[PDB]
Amino acid sequence: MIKVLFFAQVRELVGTDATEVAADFPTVEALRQHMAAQSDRWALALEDGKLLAAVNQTLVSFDHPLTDGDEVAFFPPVTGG
Amino acid sequence: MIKVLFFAQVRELVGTDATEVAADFPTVEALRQHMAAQSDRWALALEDGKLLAAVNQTLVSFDHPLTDGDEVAFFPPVTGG
Amino acid sequence: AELSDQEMLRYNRQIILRGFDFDGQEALKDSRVLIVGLGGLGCAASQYLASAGVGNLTLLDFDTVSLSNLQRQTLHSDATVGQPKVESARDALTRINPHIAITPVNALLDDAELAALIAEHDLVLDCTDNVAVRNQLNAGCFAAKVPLVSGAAIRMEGQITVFTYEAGVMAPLIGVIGSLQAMEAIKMLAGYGKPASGKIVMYDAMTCQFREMKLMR
Amino acid sequence: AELSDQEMLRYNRQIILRGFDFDGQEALKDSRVLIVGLGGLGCAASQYLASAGVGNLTLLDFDTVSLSNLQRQTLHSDATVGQPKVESARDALTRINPHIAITPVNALLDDAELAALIAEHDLVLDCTDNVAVRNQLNAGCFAAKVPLVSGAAIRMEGQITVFTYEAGVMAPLIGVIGSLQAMEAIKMLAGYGKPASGKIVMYDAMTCQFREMKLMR
Ligand SMILES: Nc1ncnc2c1ncn2[C@@H]1O[C@H](COP(=O)(O)OP(=O)(O)OP(=O)(O)O)[C@@H](O)[C@H]1O
Ligand SMILES: Nc1ncnc2c1ncn2[C@@H]1O[C@H](COP(=O)(O)OP(=O)(O)OP(=O)(O)O)[C@@H](O)[C@H]1O
Image (cartoon, rainbow over all chains, first blue to last red):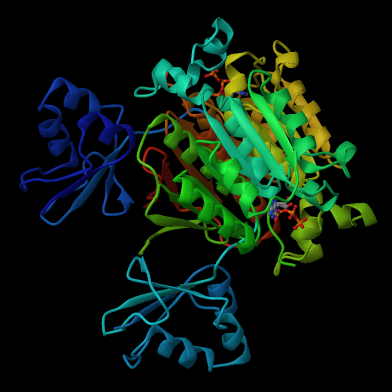
């Protein structure tokens, strides 16, 4: 279906590592809002500006076209060190 | 078929990272000798005692049963540091 | 437990980590870890076990420092060449953190003696270079049921594995693997995160790739 | 190039690595690397760039040492708190290897000045904590066409990427990522192995997993 994976702090906040979801998002940004609307914890975990999307082993814009079978991973960006 | 992968020093010596081969080895040890018989460089790269076999994401004895579709990776063992 | 005002400031960046908090930092202080092999890896791993705050560490090695070792063992120095490794290391380590208690043990213990020693700690670090020792360790640790964070490296290849129960070597490789160990140790000690027991994480420097392979009994 | 009898002994374990040999070790000696940010990562990476043998290193940071930093920046110490980081670091580094030439630069250069500096080295190390700087770097490096080994870490997460063209932080994480950088740098400098350009290697400490994700222009 749509294997939505979660890494690092993102998975930490949402409490799950992966989740299959029904196909229904044109852009990656489409899925970004659905999931974020679940709760305040989800809102923050998937807050815009503080998230990075990776579509099928490759990084993509918050617009890449999503079709059924796609694997989208959501991890945060890192700066510091 | 039989996706035989190579890692670290092993891949270094054999000069290739992966190689598909015709199904024909009962034990992992069966494949171990065929490949090692190719040349002196292959003999050494895959020399018995100095090799580790990994069958489909899991480590296995030099006997695990090999069937078509199997993915066998050959990397050396590490001690030191 | 019980951090001072100064510990609480130095350890801050750790304390504020969600899930760790003051509690974690107190666990660390109360821990008694044993590092076997203060060479390439033993040196890498201890430097961060010390700075992070593990209150009690025991250095176990029978060898002495040498020139060649100075290509990768940062804890040692030209001025300490010849001196035994447990001592060169202790000195450098107590500079990194004057708050922890460091005990050096210049020797080559046998099975009876390792066993007694192991049962005296909460976690052991396999930082050796031969299966003779690695086997004693795995043996003693399993008998007393003390977690083992084992690692190895040579040439351009490393491995790390957890148990809850010549050839050259590029300098930075010992650092990758060594710091991996020190991480996993802290993870176990404070019950933070999920340990890497049940598998071997292999690191291929030549290509910079990491593989995970499931373990079997 | 041209190693002495003493360098040739100290660097041995590197020289005997197949594919590296005397040639590699001479490249390292002839290299001029620039490290920007002698904090958590800058400290981890330089310790192994120094011991391995990169002949010339330039430390660039405007900050000073502090207590909190002593939970992870091993190159610094209580005795150096307050002193600027480029200097605390240079001192510790020259202890690790009295054979290399270290140049500290206590400042905050602007674009004109970074650009001049970059064009003076063979490789740069992004060891900073903000996109302001990281962007200048990426900019200057691309203009002069100088390789960039960039890395970052925070909390329990790291990343490393190569370009050929508060929140807490667990101590050992900076070590994993830092030593990764120092490895890739050496790889580029001597043409040994295959670089990690064209992707981001991400490291998840909480679970100890590594992911590779393809980059796009
Ligand atoms: N039985 C043991 N007890 C304590 N320490 C051990 C034991 N066996 C091996 N060691 C130590 O493990 C360490 C790590 O060695 P490593 O391979 O890292 O460096 P070395 O052995 O010191 O290096 P070199 O390759 O220059 O010989 C050594 O410093 C060695 O003394
Ligand atoms: N423009 C820049 N030029 C030089 N160094 C920089 C620049 N921007 C940031 N840095 C340095 O990058 C370093 C790494 O910081 P890190 O996040 O690793 O530790 P810190 O900033 O020193 O730590 P703390 O979280 O205790 O504040 C610092 O030591 C900081 O001074």
